[PDB]
Image (tube, helix red, strand yellow):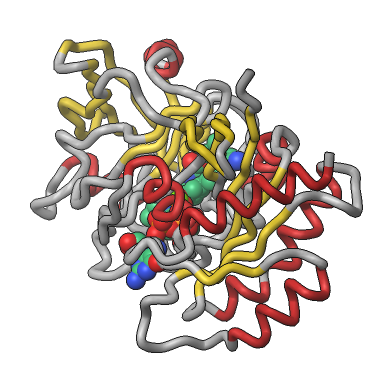
């Protein structure tokens, strides 16, 4: 049998949720920005020698559409919480997404990974130490990614699968 | 004296005529926002809605259009030389047929708009309501069959022609 993992990608506008997902699904990156409402993808992968089916829900909506996003998040078994290293608001918003996950999953212990995206950029407004401290305070992994160079992309999604497997 | 203007869209589906939708624009309560939509509908400033598509159609919620400058729903422009301020929030998203401005946050009105197909109260106070379907709500309902849960359309829904009536 092949186990299926329902992974949900959340975070503020423009942080790279879709670019990260498309790197995983389609192995490329583009500079074009196509704003998301919601898009779902499926892909078979091998993780630690075991073939697995990933369902990726790529979300959007920030606070104005958060009540609608609840319904997609309720499907998820694990979450990527994405901010961009050059976007202070996106880091300050992580708390909101964390609280939304805990509420919709009705649990204090939900598989999650903090993702600091756009690590290819030559400038940044959020310290790596801030993100490490936030992830430690949540008890979750922190992974630095770039959808542009593919740095950390597989690690972010595969780590999230391992977090799900440890929760069960 | 000036009565609230009436404008029309002739809608096409993959190039095939579907029907006409007309709108009353509430110039009496939101004159600047109504005037923008009116002038974009006639094309009298040399740009406007004619030929543009409804790039998001969400059944049970709304049909969004008005991007005549970009390919990804990020474009459009107002008649005011710049994005313009939220004029007021007097009017609410009370039910099907309401015409309201799309935006990217406060004071970012351009040309994009949406036509509600249901009451959308959660949008009150963030999107400026400025008109309402007068005739042809059945055409808007027919358009919904080509939308989906995330707004992606299965046929290309265009404003084949548009202008002012009466
Ligand atoms: C995130 C960011 O920085 N930007 C700039 C982009 C932007 O604002 N536009 C492209 C503008 C626009 O289309 N505004 C739009 C509001 C909106 C934009 C985007 O990109 C996504 C959503 C709304 C959104 C996301 C998720 C979501 C869920 C869920 N889960 C549910 N809904 C969501 C909307 C509600 C609907 C009914 C399924 C879809 O709602 C809309 O599409 C919304 C309805 C009101 C009018 N409107 N779109 C907007 O004003 C452009 C005008 C430049 C994103
Ligand atoms: N330099 C760089 N740019 C990136 C990276 N990830 C995404 N981008 C760029 O940032 C923009 C937004 O990316 P996108 O994936 O659409 O962001 P999103 O979080 O899905 N936005 P939305 O919430 O509206 O759906 C695009 O122009 C994209 O090319 C990255 O790792 N590095
Ligand atoms: Mg996206």
Q: Quadrant of residue B156?
A: top left
Q: Quadrant of the C terminus of chain B?
A: top left
For image coordinates 44% across by 54% down, the residue present is A20
Task: Specify whether residue A59 is in view.
Answer: yes
Residue B32 visible at all: no
Q: Locate residue A21, reporting x and y percent.
A: 45, 48
> Residue visible at 13% across and 50% down?
B47
The residue nearer to you, when weighing B161 against A63, is A63
Q: Quadrant of residue A59?
A: top right
Task: Establish if B126 lies above or below A54.
Answer: below
Q: Nearer the viewer, residue A145 or A96?
A: A145
> In the rendering, at what x and y percent does residue B5 appear?
34, 39
Q: Position of residue B131 (x, y in %)?
A: 46, 39
Residue found at x 44% / y 50%: A18
**Residue placed farthest to the front in the image?**
A49
Total marks in image: 0
In the image, taking residue A73 as reference, residue B2 lies left or right, namely left
Tell me where residue B6 sits by quadrant. top left
Residue located 85% across and 48% down the image: A103
- In the picture as drawn, the residue positioned furthest to the left comes out as B46
What percent of the width, then of the height, locates residue B102? 44, 49
């Amino acid at each position: 049998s092949m186990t299926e993992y329902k992974l949900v990608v959340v975070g503020a506008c423009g942080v790279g949720k879709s670019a990260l997902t498309i790197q995983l699904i389609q192995n490329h990156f583009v500079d074009e920005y196509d704003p998301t409402i919601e898009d779902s993808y499926r892909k078979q992968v091998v993780i630690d020698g075991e073939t697995s089916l990933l369902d990726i829900l790529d979300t959007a909506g920030q606070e104005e559409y958060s009540a609608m996003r609840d319904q997609y998040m309720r499907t998820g078994e694990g979450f990527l919480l994405v901010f961009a290293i050059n976007n202070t608001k996106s880091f300050e918003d992580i708390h909101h997404y964390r609280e939304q996950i805990k509420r919709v999953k009705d649990s204090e212990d939900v598989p999650m990974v903090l993702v600091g995206n756009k690590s290819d950029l030559p400038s940044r407004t959020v310290d790596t130490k801030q993100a490490q401290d936030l992830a430690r305070s949540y008890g979750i992994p922190f992974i630095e990614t770039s959808a542009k160079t593919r740095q950390g992309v597989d690690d972010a999604f595969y780590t999230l699968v391992r977090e799900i497997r440890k929760h069960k | 004296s000036m009565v609230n203007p009436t404008v029309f869209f002739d809608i096409a589906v993959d190039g095939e005529p579907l029907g006409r939708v007309s709108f009353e624009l509430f110039a009496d309560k939101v004159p600047k926002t109504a005037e923008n939509f009116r002038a974009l509908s006639t094309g009298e400033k040399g740009f406007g809605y004619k030929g543009s598509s409804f790039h998001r159609i969400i059944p049970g919620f709304m049909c969004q259009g008005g991007d005549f400058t970009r390919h990804n729903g990020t474009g459009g422009k107002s008649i005011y030389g710049e994005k313009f301020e939220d004029e007021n929030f007097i009017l609410k998203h009370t039910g099907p047929g309401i015409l309201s401005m799309a935006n990217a946050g406060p004071n970012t009105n351009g040309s994009q708009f949406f036509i509600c197909t249901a009451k959308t109260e959660w949008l009150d106070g963030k999107h400026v309501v400025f008109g309402k379907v007068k005739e042809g709500m059945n055409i808007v309902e027919a358009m919904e069959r080509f939308g989906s849960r995330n707004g992606k359309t299965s046929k290309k829904i265009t404003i084949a022609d548009c202008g002012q009536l009466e």
